[PDB]
Amino acid sequence: SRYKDNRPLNILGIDISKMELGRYNLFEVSIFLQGSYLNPFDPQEIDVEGIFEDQYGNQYRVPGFFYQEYKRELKNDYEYLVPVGDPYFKIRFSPINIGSYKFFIKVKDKTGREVSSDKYTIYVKESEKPGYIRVSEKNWRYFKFDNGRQFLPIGANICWATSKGTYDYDVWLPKCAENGGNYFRVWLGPSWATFALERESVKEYDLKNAWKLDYVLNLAEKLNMYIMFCFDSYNELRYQKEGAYPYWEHTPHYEKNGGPLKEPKDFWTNNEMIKYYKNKLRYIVARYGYSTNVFAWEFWNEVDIISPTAFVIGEVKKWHEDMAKYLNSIDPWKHLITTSFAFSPGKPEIDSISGLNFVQTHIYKSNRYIDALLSLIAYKEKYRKPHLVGEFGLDAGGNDLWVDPNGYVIHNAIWTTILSGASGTAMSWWWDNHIHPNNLYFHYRALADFVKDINFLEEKFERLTNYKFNVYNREIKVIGLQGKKYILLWLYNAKEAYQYKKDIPNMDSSKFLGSIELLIKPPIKVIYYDTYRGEKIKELDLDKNVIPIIEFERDLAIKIELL
Ligand SMILES: OC[C@H]1O[C@@H](O[C@H]2[C@H](O)[C@H](O)[C@H](O)O[C@@H]2CO)[C@@H](O)[C@@H](O)[C@@H]1O
Ligand SMILES: OC[C@H]1O[C@@H](O)[C@@H](O)[C@@H](O)[C@@H]1O
């Protein structure tokens, strides 16, 4: 209890960032106070709240959070944070309507005493921000922003940094964003993670790592990138003898290390653990919920490979139901909620929960992974909510960086997933040792430039069929979408797409390979698109339903417009 206080409850000061701001922008209040509490992260010890009301009567009850300011520096090869000033409490709000808001601050400590701040008025003007990310009501396969524009996640996992900490995100994120990336995922556990909130304790949260997460979220705000926050990872509940980067012996949850749990099975039902987990959710909502750059709350990385002594499907399901309900109830902005599994088909008992707004796949597979992605995407349409392939790679023991230094595997997967009907790109691993040093960002730029002007929410896209190849010299396969107005094709050579030794193609090729006949009504306009250079190659008007296939080395994209 290093942050305890033993004084009569009183507000000592309030600082307000600005009295005028734009729609969906951050409005921050600093609160200096004294009171009686053992743990500023526990609302039963001290509960700070901001009560906001727009001019239409809508009310928002925003929990406040304990905060320490830091100044970062780089000490040779590691980030070091110097504390600045005493810690204090903050409220972070974001207005969804324009016009006037009134708000006040309310504080209650463990004595039951309650104090209040006077009503303040702020004014909100229109801004460029599109709002929070939601499931599309027009097409449940896809995400939208509040303003109705689509959100197609294009990016990769970027889940933790080296010892350089936030300085790595300074490098990775601008490169991602300038190459069409608008998405990444970060880990808030286990305790070794860059943004670990439960670093030494499950009762009190790490103010340095929370500040690093502030920094990276602010950088995403500047770059128009949107983040999935993964709260916990399976390692926390996996025993040393079970392998796969286990961490139970080191995790703060374990009684040996000060926590409430005698064994990982008890995580799901232990009353003390559930209480502190809800305090963590409240802290996360308080500190980060305002941000439209939070794409989603993700409870678990691969919860199915916690210790087999700890995975009880009925209890994990109930815990996800209860925590999703709680999180929704306290999150004024109702961010999307999800969870993930190592087993690529997932766990239907959990994926079917209505409180999980979208489902995910993790898949590491070396052989015929294009077909495996297609099959999984087709299968999970049964949930009638969006599907994110949140992790993807070879099953090569982490050797992708030297088996495939050109990123052909990533290339194949991001084209396959977005043109099979998934909500966005397959999300690669290996951001730090592969994507960045091998400079693989250009793959994403080529894909983003192909899809960005299509409104997927209105095309009524269906996976391509009723097609007939007529190709004699090669084995060419197709992944395709057929919509109201567009047909999008990704063609690949089955005998070249899975070999990674040759250099990046630079076709000069103008040559005729074969044809693909589609059941569509002509006339049409056909655009041939280089998937490595990210450029239109050729354009052709047609009066029949048979599209010539021009020469290409590994794969080729075609955009067809029904006229
Ligand atoms: O290297 C940093 C952390 O790696 C962690 O293991 C990772 C591992 O690097 C790899 O990405 C693997 O497939 O997923 C693991 C996490 O589940 C931990 O070993 C951690 O201790 C390291 O700091
Ligand atoms: O920032 C990502 C990486 O960039 C490299 O050039 C080095 O500086 C690494 O130390 C760093 O982790």
Image (tube, rainbow, N blue to C red):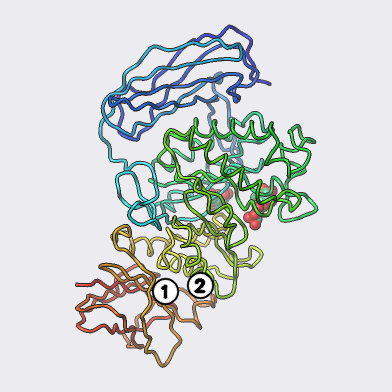
Q: Quadrant of residue 529?
A: bottom left
In-image side of 191 versus 282 (left or right): right
Q: Is residue 77 visible?
A: no
At mark 2, the secondary structure is: helix
CB within 8 Å, label 2 to label 1: yes
Identify residue type, mark 1: Ile
Mark 1 beta carbon near ligand 1 (under 8 Å) = no
**Element marked by disc 1:** strand
Q: Position of residue 401 (x, y in %)?
A: 58, 65
Specify the quadrant that holds the C terminus. Answer: bottom left
Residue denoted by label 1: 479
Picture layout, residue 484 above or below residue 152: below
Q: Tell me the crowding category of disc 1: few under 14, some 14 to 19, or many 20 or more residues within 10 angstroms, Cα based.
A: many
Does 102 sit above or below residue 464? above
Q: Position of residue 306 (x, y in %)?
A: 69, 51
Q: Percent from the top left, x then y, of residue 234?
A: 66, 49
Task: Classify 5 as above or below 271.
Answer: above
Task: From the viewer's side, name the closer residue of 245 and 176.
Answer: 245
Classed neighbour count for the residue bearing mark 2: other residues with Cα under 10 Å, few (<14), some (14–19), many (≥20): many
Inspect the image, locate mark 2, and give the three-letter code of the amino acid beneath it: Ile
Q: Which mark is residue 546?
A: none
Whether residue 486 is visible, yes or no, is: yes
Residue that appears at 69% across and 31% down = 272
| Mark nearer the N terminus (2 vs 1) | 2
- Residue at which label 2 appears: 370
Q: Residue at x 58, y 63 (%)?
A: 345
User: Is 317 or 160 nearer to us in this picture?
Assistant: 317
The part of the image, by quadrant, that contains residue 95 is: top left
Q: Is residue 96 left or right of residue 241?
A: left
Q: Closer to the camera, 235 or 310? A: 310
- Between residue 408 and residue 344, name the one nearer to us: 344
